[PDB]
Amino acid sequence: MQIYEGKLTAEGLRFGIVASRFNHALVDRLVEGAIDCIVRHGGREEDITLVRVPGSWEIPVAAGELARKEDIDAVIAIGVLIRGATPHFDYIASEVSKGLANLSLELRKPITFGVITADTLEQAIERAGTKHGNKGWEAALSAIEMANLFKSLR
Amino acid sequence: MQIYEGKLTAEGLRFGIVASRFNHALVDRLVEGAIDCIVRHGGREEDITLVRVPGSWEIPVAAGELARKEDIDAVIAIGVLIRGATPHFDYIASEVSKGLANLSLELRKPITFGVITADTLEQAIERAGTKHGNKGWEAALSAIEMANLFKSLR
Amino acid sequence: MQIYEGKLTAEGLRFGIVASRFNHALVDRLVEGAIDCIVRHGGREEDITLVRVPGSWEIPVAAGELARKEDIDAVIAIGVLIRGATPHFDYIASEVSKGLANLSLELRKPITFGVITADTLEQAIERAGTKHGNKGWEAALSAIEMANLFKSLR
Amino acid sequence: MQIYEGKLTAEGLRFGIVASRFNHALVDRLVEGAIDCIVRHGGREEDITLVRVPGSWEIPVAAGELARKEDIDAVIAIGVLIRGATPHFDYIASEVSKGLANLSLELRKPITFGVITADTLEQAIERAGTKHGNKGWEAALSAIEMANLFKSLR
Amino acid sequence: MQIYEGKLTAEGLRFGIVASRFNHALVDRLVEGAIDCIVRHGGREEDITLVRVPGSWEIPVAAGELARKEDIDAVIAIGVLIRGATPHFDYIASEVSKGLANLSLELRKPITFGVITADTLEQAIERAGTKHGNKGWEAALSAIEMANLFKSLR
Amino acid sequence: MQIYEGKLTAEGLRFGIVASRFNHALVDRLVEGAIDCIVRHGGREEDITLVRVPGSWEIPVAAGELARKEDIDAVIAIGVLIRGATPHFDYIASEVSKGLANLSLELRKPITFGVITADTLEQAIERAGTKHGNKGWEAALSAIEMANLFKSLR
Amino acid sequence: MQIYEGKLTAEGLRFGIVASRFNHALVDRLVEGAIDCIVRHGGREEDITLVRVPGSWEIPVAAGELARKEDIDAVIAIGVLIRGATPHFDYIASEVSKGLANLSLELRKPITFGVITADTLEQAIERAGTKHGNKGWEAALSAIEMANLFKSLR
Ligand SMILES: O=Nc1c(NC[C@H](O)[C@H](O)[C@H](O)CO)[nH]c(=O)[nH]c1=O
Ligand SMILES: O=Nc1c(NC[C@H](O)[C@H](O)[C@H](O)CO)[nH]c(=O)[nH]c1=O
Ligand SMILES: O=Nc1c(NC[C@H](O)[C@H](O)[C@H](O)CO)[nH]c(=O)[nH]c1=O
Ligand SMILES: O=Nc1c(NC[C@H](O)[C@H](O)[C@H](O)CO)[nH]c(=O)[nH]c1=O
Ligand SMILES: O=Nc1c(NC[C@H](O)[C@H](O)[C@H](O)CO)[nH]c(=O)[nH]c1=O
Ligand SMILES: O=Nc1c(NC[C@H](O)[C@H](O)[C@H](O)CO)[nH]c(=O)[nH]c1=O
Ligand SMILES: O=Nc1c(NC[C@H](O)[C@H](O)[C@H](O)CO)[nH]c(=O)[nH]c1=O
């Protein structure tokens, strides 16, 4: 059987992170986790490109520009959506996730999903560096693995 | 009437399996089922290519690379999604299923769906080699049928 | 370790199917599934012998005649029992299952069990080609596996 | 595909009927139905052998003697069990059905089941020539079919 | 039509009775009824062989020895089972009835069933010489009929 | 007093294991336990013969072939039955246990019972390597003891 | 990978058992199990040293003396604590378990835990040779494994 997989050492890997500013008190924890994951897995901080955008709605268009760079191996999408009173949350969550997934396939490059889509503020806190981990750290780890995988797969 | 169908003998067929690591204790049973189905239907294990990715989110982009290979007749997607407290599950389940379906049409190649999308852990267990079967085995059997069908249809 | 197993290709295998007429609108779907399973697994339809009997009660005695044939590799028992108002169902279900199992051991030949024993009509429909599969297809697949296994085991 | 089945014309067929006397007011209707079914399907009444026994318990041992006769093509078992206050009914119903089924397999000869096993008197009446038919007639029709089937199968 | 039946005169008939000692205050009434039935139907008491055993569990093995005697025309099994707190009753009732039925078929000799299987003590009393008759008397009458029947049938 | 018993050291003992594939995610743990029990009790893995069958229904006929081998000292039956919506479970559980027990007596060779018969999935998990142990390990230990016992007893 | 494990044959192994007298009617069953486990796994009974003490409280200080013996390979602690009306149970259960564990580490020698700590008498009975096994047998089996493991590990 042929088996392809990615290791978790990030030596030489270059990452794009797109992080939204809405709910920054939480997003900022996700960005810390992502960078920490990259660096302590051996990636250089100098090899990270961070792009900030207003909200989750704007993440895809910026990710699309990063993912098109030949010297970016994977993109990590980071944001925090918390449900308000209207279905505003639903349309933005739907389109951010669809855009990111579509770009990854179109550009044949890993784009990982560190966007929280929480019904409540408490759930968002849980996932931004507390009891349910740090989704930035998780999405970065996935990007490490995928970039390594893609060295042989792509 | 012209009738086209695929038999279930897998002699000479070559398969790509993309399997996620999230919920591996269940995904690993799905992979065992898929391989077993292929091998005991006459497919050679050497003609199987297994690609591992972090989570169901990452299955599509890897499947896209496999399905593009001229020496892969069909791709089998294997993963396990279990609903958490937030709609995180919904956005990932939606995008994994849409990506896989879109890729299949774009590449004109069968990509089968052995991704469990369960509301509960119990339901996932049921479908990963217990009372409700093994979705890996099922998706592999579908891929056998489709690859054979495609020998005359494509 | 010595390991014996049966593959699922049916080339050269010869099957007996005994199917009851009671509840034929469901039994007939089970017979379709059994024949389809055999044929698309590489067995020839000519190599199938189908014996029809009135009810599940009469399946064992017919199966006994088929299983004694040297050119029958396995027998597939197909019928549909649905509970009525009295324990009639219990005595027939008990005896059909015991007879088939006893014959298999006495004749040292696989006899598989595609007899539905349902409490309700809905449950029978579920198992005769709808949401819970086709018990004829399942019993045929088992018979394929057992006949192959028996080529080395018997 | 080889197909074996029994037609429903009874010309030249010879039947054994074993009928118990317990609950005779209902068993007697079952015997009328069985004979009528045979005769109007073309069987001669002279070719019917009727054996009377006390209760359903005694049906098997008498059926064993009839089924051993070379000039009997099939045996029809007729009796009526209605649940009393104790499990007496369960042990008799279990043993009558098991004995009959066992004899059929041991002697390789059809023995059909026109024994009512009712929880209530009403249910027994329903099945002895009223709204739910006549189980004697039914069991006779099955024996006609099986004897014909056995002309080629046995 | 050929018709076989047994009359109820017991002249010249020889019977075996196997009676258990558990619940003897009731079993003893069953033995009185059995002997009375035989004698007043014309059988000689000298032609009766009574075998006593500890409990219903031991009835079959003793009945097996009696029924094998060429000078015994039928065996009458007599015992009293009353449900206790555990399923002990179920396993013994099941096996006594199965053994007796099996022996009758194996030895091609009538063995009648005068074993009470009662849920309550009251039910046992009812059936041991009170309002619901005497099961010993009943089983003896059946044995008379069967022995006579067997003079022509066996 | 003469006392016969089996020790638990398995040096030189040869075992047959028959394992069903239905509910393999659990059966596979039972097989691990059985093999582990044999090997760490001093049995050689080379002296184990493993036979795979589709379902619990098919275990008896395969076990019958293994148990007939003069170089097999005991057979371990391993399977997992979990109750569905219908009495299907009952008829299979009944016949698997009956067949195995009957074969053991007919062949005068130990056949041990490592078949789980659970009302719920949770109960099956409990007994397949979690809180209520591993029934494969247990049945193997029993087979070790019985094979040793049989060295003097048989 | 280097892998260390203990087999379950006890040839040549020498055990210390410390058993308390409080609740002896249960403890005595635990001691029976422990000795039986050892002996039937190949250990000699002569190689067992049994030390009796008044209550679970006193088990540690005795185990400390046994575990210091160079010719003792492992110590098995056996006792039965059942909750009374006061927290007396808690303080003794806490100190017995702590002492044993501490001794094991200090002396670098396996000391296994066959002390029942039951809320009820029923629970104690269950674990002292009835439905939930025999904790003496379990703790002995552990000690056999650990002593063997320690032959390479220590
Ligand atoms: O509204 N709540 C959220 C949000 N709204 C802003 C939106 O993404 C966009 O910036 C504006 O619609 C303008 O285009 N953006 C988030 O990241 N999280 C939220 O929870
Ligand atoms: O969250 N639950 C699940 C999960 N999340 C991980 C996700 O697929 C992706 O790896 C990350 O978002 C990073 O891109 N992936 C699954 O396969 N199943 C789940 O049940
Ligand atoms: O009654 N219901 C059922 C039925 N009774 C007919 C029976 O098997 C037999 O043919 C007669 O007793 C005559 O011997 N047979 C079935 O297969 N399914 C049923 O649900
Ligand atoms: O009891 N109820 C029934 C009955 N008991 C008699 C029994 O079959 C046997 O004749 C005696 O036990 C003596 O051997 N026999 C029936 O056919 N139907 C019944 O409903
Ligand atoms: O237990 N209750 C009953 C009983 N138990 C004894 C049993 O038959 C046997 O003798 C012993 O198990 C020893 O083999 N025997 C009966 O006839 N009736 C009962 O109601
Ligand atoms: O249905 N549930 C179960 C199952 N049915 C399959 C059956 O044993 C047999 O393979 C078929 O009837 C074909 O003969 N087999 C099991 O081992 N466990 C189950 O829980
Ligand atoms: O009290 N109940 C228990 C008990 N008390 C005695 C105690 O261990 C000690 O011997 C005295 O305190 C004197 O030192 N010892 C037990 O083993 N089990 C009990 O359930």
Image (cartoon, coloured by chain):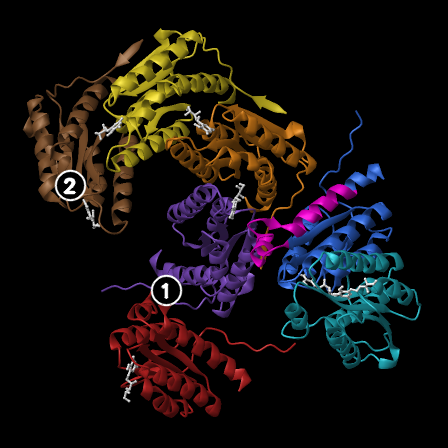
Chain colours: A cyan, B blue, C orange, D yellow, E brown, F purple, G red
Q: Please give the name of the residue rendered at 48% of the width and 38% of the height, measured from the top-left corner.
A: C104
Marks 2 & 1, CB-CB < 8 Å contact = no
| Quarter assignment of residue A37 | bottom right
Report the quarter where the N terminus of chain D lies: top right
Q: Please give the name of the residue rendered at 62% of the width and 59% of the height, measured from the top-left corner.
A: B26
Type of amino acid at the residue the image marks with label 2: Glu
Based on the picture, tell me whether residue B127 belongs to the magenta stretch: yes
| Quarter assignment of residue E66 | top left
Marking on residue E122: 2
Along the horizontal axis of the image, is E121 left or right of A38? left
Along the horizontal axis of the image, is E109 left or right of C23? left
Residue B139's place in the image compared with F12, above or below, is: above
Could you tell me residue F109's position as x and y percent? 40, 52
Task: Determine whether the residue tagged by mark 2 lies in a helix, strand or loop.
Answer: helix
Q: Badge 1 is on which residue?
A: F6
Could you tell me residue B128's position as x and y percent? 61, 54
Residue D33's place in the image compared with C143, above or below, is: above
Q: Which residues are magenta?
A: B118-147
Q: Crowdedness of circle 2 by 10 Å Cα count: few (<14), some, many (20+)?
A: few
